Amino acid sequence: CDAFVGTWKLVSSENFDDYMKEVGVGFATRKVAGMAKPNMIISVNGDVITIKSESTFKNTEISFILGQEFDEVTADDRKVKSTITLDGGVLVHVQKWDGKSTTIKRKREDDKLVVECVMKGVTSTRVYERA
Image (cartoon, rainbow, N blue to C red):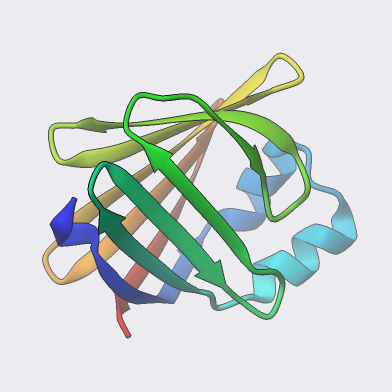
């Protein structure tokens, strides 16, 4: 996961409002969350990977071991069960709650970190560059 390690800044966001709609995020949270230009800080210490997001909307931090389910309270306040695995270089993060599931994929592409958020038929692409 060393290629992911670093401080990253959001530079573009496509279809994020529609992704959040599909997830079930309410109007006011969608509007405020949609404006944010977060920094994502990724670090590794042994088997533990930490992903921190710092933004004007709200700060989050998750630490996890690959393949091992954990509790996550998301920025939009869902209480989800999360599992993150590595699939041929891509971090695959599945969140489950209320009989629903969404998948967030994080991958390195050129000098960018590309985040693909999928909820049923709706995909949002968020691109980060090194801070």
